[PDB]
Amino acid sequence: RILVECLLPNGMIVTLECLREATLITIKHELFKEARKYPLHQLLQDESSYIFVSVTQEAEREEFFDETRRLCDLRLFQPFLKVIEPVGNREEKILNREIGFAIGMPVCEFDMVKDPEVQDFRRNILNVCKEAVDLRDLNSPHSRAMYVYPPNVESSPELPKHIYNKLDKGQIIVVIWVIVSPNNDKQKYTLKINHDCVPEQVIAEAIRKKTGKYILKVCGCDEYFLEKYPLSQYKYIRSCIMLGRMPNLMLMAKESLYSQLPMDCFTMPSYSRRETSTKSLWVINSALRIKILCATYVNVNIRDIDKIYVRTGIYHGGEPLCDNVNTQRVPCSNPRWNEWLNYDIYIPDLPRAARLCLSICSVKGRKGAKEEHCPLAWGNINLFDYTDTLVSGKMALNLWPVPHGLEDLLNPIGVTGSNPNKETPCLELEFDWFSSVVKFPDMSVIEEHANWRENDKEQLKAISTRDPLSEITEQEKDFLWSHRHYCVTIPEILPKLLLSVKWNSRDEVAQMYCLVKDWPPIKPEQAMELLDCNYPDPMVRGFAVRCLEKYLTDDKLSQYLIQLVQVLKYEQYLDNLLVRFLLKKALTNQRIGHFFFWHLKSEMHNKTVSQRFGLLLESYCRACGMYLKHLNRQVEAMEKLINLTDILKQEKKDETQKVQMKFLVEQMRRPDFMDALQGFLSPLNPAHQLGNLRLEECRIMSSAKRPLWLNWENPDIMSELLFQNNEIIFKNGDDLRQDMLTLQIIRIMENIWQNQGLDLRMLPYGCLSIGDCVGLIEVVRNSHTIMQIQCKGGNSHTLHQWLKDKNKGEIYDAAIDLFTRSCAGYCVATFILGIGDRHNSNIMVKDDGQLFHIDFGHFLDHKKKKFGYKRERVPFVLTQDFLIVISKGAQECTKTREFERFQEMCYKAYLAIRQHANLFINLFSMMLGSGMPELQSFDDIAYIRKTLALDKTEQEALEYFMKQMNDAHHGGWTTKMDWIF
Amino acid sequence: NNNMSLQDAEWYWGDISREEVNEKLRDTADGTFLVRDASTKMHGDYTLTLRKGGNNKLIKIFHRDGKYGFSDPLTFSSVVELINHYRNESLAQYNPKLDVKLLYPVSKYQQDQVVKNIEAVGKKLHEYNTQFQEKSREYDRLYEEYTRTSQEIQMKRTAIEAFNETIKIFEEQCQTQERYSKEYIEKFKREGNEKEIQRIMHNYDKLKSRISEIIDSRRRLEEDLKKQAAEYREIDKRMNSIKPDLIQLRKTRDQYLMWLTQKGVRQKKLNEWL
């Protein structure tokens, strides 16, 4: 029973009993039906002239043009309907409503701001938005399917040699399903074809043996073959080749694909349409000067502290340009300073990316001789704005709370700008007024500001090979700067050369700019490290973005998408080259754009980057197109799932699970849940379509916080060949950013081992965080925990007898070797990264013999750092249960090849990762500011530096590794299987 | 002084990596320095670190031909010789950019002499651990409370904005109906129908009652908002009060653990048994 108090425009009201399922059509009809009985009915105009408006639950007076939308999902405030005349068009208003619903907060807040940077970014990003939109329509209708269904191919057309021998003389047996004409029936043809074949001659051969005209499709989901690539380059084909599976493909009609694919249109919003010589900054001759006027109020006691002060200093990234300058300690009762502050830095020596990092610290004398300090709040100010003007004049800055687990006085790597809240400690600033506007000099002043061989090059290459966080000395810095003109032959040395220069100068910074402007392009992985917080210069980041534009491919872009999203926070200004490149790539690839949207959507609970990401979702949702419907459906499903969880996680702690199951099923009898949970693409993979929602296998388990198990029938026409049921665990209350990072690193390590020539394959399943401690986990069918395996088995031979009776015969040895290879891969991975300890439940074993780990926590040994002790821990200890399988139950391992093969494959994996460790160093360096407790600074990356033994050479790294994995195993791991020299 | 050995030298340090150097050389005065063995583990190489210009530097010491020195040519037969030479002489002639002396050496002797029966110190450290863990549990629980309370502050903030918007839309409706109703009441009062006039008083009374109800709701919600903001400020004050003693106990526990480690007794394999 819902009572809605309507508000007629002529001054009367009505208390009407409104049905739950009734829409606004019936509301308006029965409203005007009884209007005639009421007085003054003649004044009413036609229904068209009047449109209902109200205030929503999310605190905004949002127009209601969606006349056909139901009453339940109106997200309304206190029930009342207001009648006004229309004051604009309808299409853009519906678009804005949908965009605001997708993002989470309405676009009205984005429109009602006074900051010129936000408005300029909103006005200027639409240029690249419309450019990408017209680019996607250049090859219509082919380009429409190109955008909607982009090929999932690999970067290089060349096939690795170690798997070419797995084929039947470099050829693939291919099965091609096809509908005859009256539908139904099972008609199968199978064809034999090589690997470097192209789909047009594939369909040509299929047609010519049957007796731009047809298209392929992977059976079960929506994957299509469009572009001129070798058939083996596609991920599905490669996966089937690795798995030894027959690749099931079906033949469709291109006209049907073009017909079912909807049109795309981009509409320009209404806000889209809405001399002097000056003196350069390098002519001012005066030190930088700051005045701290007062702090409005701080949250500190009187009888627990004595005196406070402000700890401030100039920075460039994380490297201070000068020593920290303090103020006189005033009492905390009256935070008034009025003290001018001088720095040992001149104005012309200020770099473009300079910052002003400040914090409020409390000093406690104590009875101890040394005094301690404790920050109250922190705040960062850019000394320049987006228009390249030095900040000046009166300014008030709001201060952020100190992050948990951070004890350093300042927070130089943090978001620049004021806290949006007004109930926060506000510090008063003041800058020197130069009686004009001081602007950073243009490119000409830098360009013509400047200009005012021995065989001992092995040192340059030697320091190039070392990791970005390796030990670097001022002798090395002087050598690097002296021979910078000879560094062109080794483009690897660019990050080290950048770190060699000190940024509190002018002439050498100009020389560095001249060098970078002519730098040869480098590898995308080598230029991706130039995007972390250690390189804040706009020219360096522009060069890195140019390298990514030139050389990075879509597969690798989807590989490193999460870190690329992460390094958007380190950008000081809203409009920059990186975000333009990311938006151009997300608007030409629906698969990339989907994950882009979901990553940014997850990263808005943090208010530090809420606005700069909300604007991104706004722009993309304006320019994405027809994908808004699927995104809205996914968002509705996810938010209803969040409601379903949090109505039970906190309110039903003290009851039994039976009442919880009754509660869950009685809401699963409410038609709204079924109505919303149908026919929407899975956020984990847009290629999957989720059909009906069964209830016979959707429940909760006995875990710590009752994750939700959900199953969806596959609605594909020939879904029988592939997986029949899609299972997803909806986990609430556990952060999944660390799990996503762990699975990503596992995926790169698996790719590295496969490319190297080892079958050290793992199972990097799908994870996706969708917000605050909420995310989706893709679960694997026909997999069991070792705990329940040994529970049903029973003692030490239970897993061995399980692998015996599950697949006996000639396939037993295949199961054994697959188990060995997976176990070796996960041993190496869990040792190197440092994931928390493994249990019986954490290890998951497949039916065919593969094993994998499902539960991940902290990765850089964060949980065991409570007690200070420098040591290396091996979580994945090989219990005797696994050694039975590795040695096939042998009494002695001294006359079996399996033990030495396992040893050498582990050593080869370790050497491969130690050779490719630069990628992992760069990834954990780029993922620093995510806010994880386990990854807050470079001291955490020191752990991954010392587990791989970067400082030790390749010789004693082996001995260190065996020491770790034998004193963790209580011995048993000795000597070398073959002596090379 | 004299030619006292390298092992007992104040500035020299043992098996030391970057993170503890940064821990000791954090927010210290200019010129502060120490010497530790190089991470390359080459025999008798050593590296000199000093905090000049606000950031930690890393001077390398060369050991070519059994002689020490910063660069070719080497002119010191021992590390102590050039350490004292550059302590008593500025580095201006060596490098035009770098101009600093080795003023304040980092010495462990202070922490060695201010620390001051094995069972007694073992139980003292156990009690320190218990106090640290209970204080950290209180810190975590109250930090969760602080974050949650901020969430409810935001929630009633949005509630106040929605109530305010409703108030403005209702007052705008009242103003519009007053402006567009004064030009039709003349005919109504000339014809004189009591029923419709009674209806207009009844409707205006109901509307004003609803306005009063929503105004009361807004006032009580803003009272709840301000009292919860006061509680939030009190929680923040408690945070700032309990941070520094927590970190001081953390340093004390680390110092005791390092003293126990350098004493050579392995307490990790016995304390856990309890």
Image (tube, coloured by chain):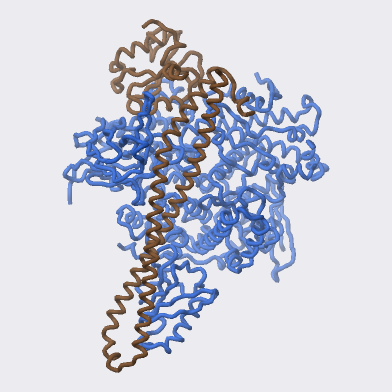
Chain colours: A blue, B brown
Q: Is residue A452 above or below residue A244?
A: above
| Front residue of A860 and B219 | B219
Q: Is residue B136 above or below residue A36?
A: above
Question: Which corner quadrant holds the N terminus of chain A?
Answer: bottom right
- The residue at the point 65 percent across, 63 percent down is A665
Can residue A220 be seen in this snapshot?
A: no
Q: Is residue A398 left or right of residue A568?
A: left
Q: Is residue A625 left or right of residue A120?
A: right
| Front residue of A845 and A227 | A845
Can residue A423 be seen in this snapshot?
A: yes
The spot of residue A575 in percent (x, y) is 36, 50
Question: Which corner quadrant holds the C terminus of chain A?
Answer: top right
The spot of residue B2 in percent (x, y) is 38, 5
Q: Is residue A350 above or below residue B189?
A: above
- The residue at the point 60 percent across, 26 percent down is B271
Labels in figure, total: 0
Extreme-left residue of the structure? A435
| Front residue of A201 and A683 | A683
Q: Is residue A207 left or right of residue A497?
A: right
Extreme-bottom residue of the structure? B191
Dividing the picture into quadrants, the one containing residue A164 is top right
Q: Is residue A969 above or below residue A411?
A: above
The spot of residue B144 in percent (x, y) is 49, 46
Dividing the picture into quadrants, the one containing residue A261 is bottom right
Extreme-top residue of the structure? B2
The spot of residue B248 in percent (x, y) is 44, 30
